[PDB]
Image (cartoon, rainbow, N blue to C red; front, side, top):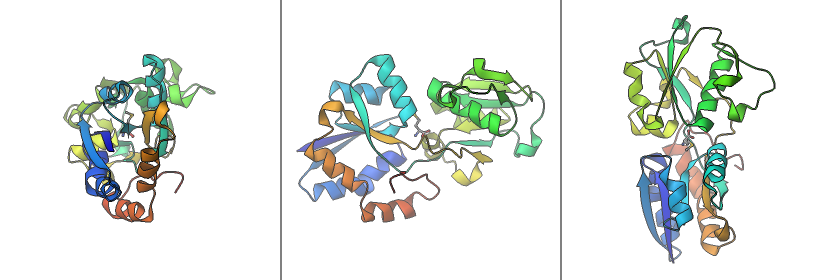
Length: 239
Ligand code: MET
């Protein structure tokens, strides 16, 4: 049986090629990997049938996308994830913020919400009490304490937005594939609500191949591999 994986390019793809694929092949499976540079296509390819499983998103994004596009897909298990971080842009230290400082952020809703929550924790802005952090939007800002100019861009353009803004909040997969290091972040999201999940069409939730893939991502072997290959990543809660 052939298992077709869809992942964003870089780390999640490497997990498959370097570790998961060889493990599944020892069980007779032929594995195919399709890598994407964007966040939009994977879930569509999954629902269409082109992919049997994808690994590139967190639950809030999945939930948002599924609803918006009415797709019968669901999460299965979590994977080691590169954490979200606020990195040095033109300014190199949090201490250097000032009135009007610019901060770049991804512009899709589920990820943008994360930037606002991070700015609230830094005390740069103040979010209204009782709002859903998962859906925080500009309308949820009670006071822009430091008059921060939040610059929004397509998620993939964040690493290089650093040349044009004081600070840049970059998604981990893009930070890593752009030559950035997690240790370079000035502040990292403390939350664990965004550790990424693999997704599949609901129809395959109980399949045998998915059971094999699932244990391949949770064996001691994988855990050892992950510990040395992806230092600094947030681990699946189940671990
Ligand atoms: C498509 S949702 C964003 C996924 C990305 N790997 C992150 O954890 O920030």
